[PDB]
Image 1 (tube, rainbow, N blue to C red):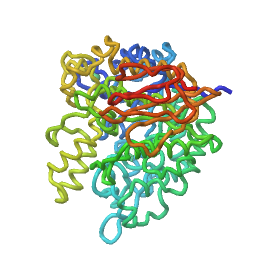
Image 2 (cartoon, rainbow, N blue to C red; image 1 turned 90 degrees about the vertical axis):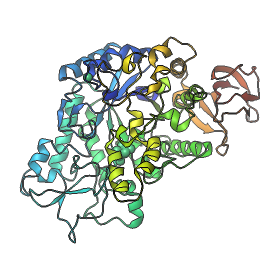
Image 3 (cartoon, rainbow, N blue to C red; image 1 turned 90 degrees about the horizontal axis):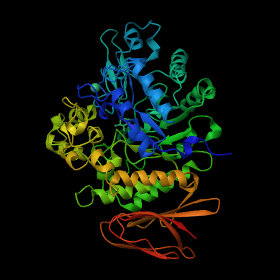
Image 4 (cartoon, helix red, strand yellow; image 1 turned 180 degrees about the horizontal axis):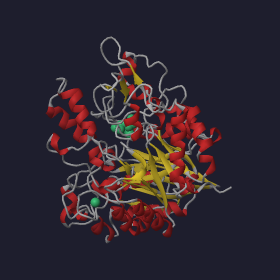
Length: 556
Ligand SMILES: OC[C@H]1O[C@H](O)[C@H](O)[C@@H](O)[C@@H]1O
Ligand SMILES: [Ca+2]
């Protein structure tokens, strides 16, 4: 039995808001995405995941949805969504949409009804509780600042919001609510959608009675919110009432969950989700407060990958990504975005990304080696989470505005959201108007038109790696083995299938390094290298590596 198409595919994530504008309002749209499908096809992309594209007041850029069955006004009409689908299908490409059902907009008609009275039939579509001892029902905090509880004077109770005030949590404990969600999913799957990605999938079940978080839990609240006791019962039911009747792949954003629980979401025998996005790697260097960085080494990086791979085992399956719309840019985060090293390290990270056991997701603009943005003031951020940090840390006197700026510049989601850099015309060819978020000035050196025409570019290297992955089954579905998990200079591992073995070797230092193959192993062939003056000789038992050198080798 061949493995399903999604185990061997290469995905690309599109953040439609920041991808391509076609009417000069400074916001990307569907017509912009549709016009650029030949660009993604030519790169070799099999499937696209688009961030939320539904009716939204955009307090959280699409993740506050006010109608699940209509398209966002800024992106276009249902006709434009249908045309997008038809053009993907022409190119043999698939669509994964984002599914945001932990919470809705406070502007959704369900919520406008829910708020009206305790006896409203929509009351229990959300969570409403009396406050305690003069204040909120409990001490839950929100990821976006202040309490996770908001008082509504219309009834005098509080409603739950893990995310923003304008994102009330949906009440999965209510059967009528679940049934409404399942019908909504069927609405999109009936249109032929090939995949669904579940935003914060691990927080759907709430703790009965909502007791206070202990001081430990408080310091790690993201984790406590993943511990609802009905979580897997809900996911199994969603599979039985929705996914079982379609041919779609399902991927969960398992944010906050302890790694050893991940198998419950993805083990195929459990009939929950097909694949996981986990955050142990991408947050391995993030403080608990989410706005400081802690220094880590390559040893921490590879050890995390190893543990994550082990949790997928025989019946589970992982995605692999180094960036998304909620994190800093891959090259700035994991490589070295200084001008002399940006290109060399962007290539090394590509090699890593495209040779992991798992379905790779390439975040828009990483194929160009786009970097973090040079924020100068707090006013340069759009992000609602940065306003939250301002509220929780600056106004309470815990940190100065400057301490916030300096640290959040490195970590903020807005680093990923600056407009895609198409060429060196005005605003990098993203828009003819004023972009909703400023273009990085480095667009003059980093842009698609320049990259595409250059066979030594980062783009070209990504295109070649993708082609090599497509051609070499061991690189998608073969086993993974880290050759030396404690080495903090040179990342090396094998991928193996049906007697064939490939060796990947990646120098994480901006300094020359040596690598000795394990005993009995010799180089048979060189598939590709980055930043290398010469391939090893057939039979080679060791390698000399330039700074940031990467390579893939068939081994014997
Ligand atoms: O808690 C899940 C979500 O919370 C916030 O949005 C985080 O910034 C983001 O990483 C994640 O998608
Ligand atoms: Ca537009």
